[PDB]
Length: 301
Image (cartoon, rainbow, N blue to C red):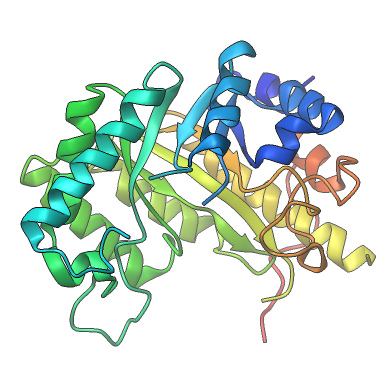
């Protein structure tokens, strides 16, 4: 029946929801109906409270992401790290009852292939380097000894960045950082990563972590027609083909939004298994009924 049900033995089937979706009675009934995992989407933490409570009273697993000033003043590494641990341990304590997994660090790696330094030169990095990741996981492991702790990134399937994610997560785990898991965001498209590209990403992440979530599943169209519903349906099937192949390491597959109406990609990107009216799509059937794709992966521009 529900997606969460069909896959009740491969992985949690999850969605990122904002406050409207668990506020709107009808969107909430769908979430309840389709998912056994909720990421707080919202990428004064009232929102994290509502999403958490929704999971609380409805017994849905919560993927901590939502919440996790603090560098505008150019703190010293030391002070930045106390602000980290504070926030991290605050965020984590308030929801360790519901949150089973945390995106402790997001998108620390750069997308630039032509970059000597594989980390995104984010403000956090410019202060601290590698060790803000280390600290972030140490702080979070400490605050909840428990929550699988996920390094979460996107374009996790392209050759270079993925190697960097792997290598960064390898050496940090090698150095003992509590990186329990790797979160493949899953912001794919209809031309997407190929099955082997996701296969080659998961099989690589497999070899250093016992947990891969798909945290932010999204399949934007064009990097509605018949061409479009099949391409969307087909790449979803392709993705869920490779995900249900790695069901062991993959504990959770979270779609990035309840529907195209909510999608960060915009509805014209037709990205999720529910159209803007939350009618399931042929993509939804293709995933539910574990179908294989019709056409092969479309060619790109």
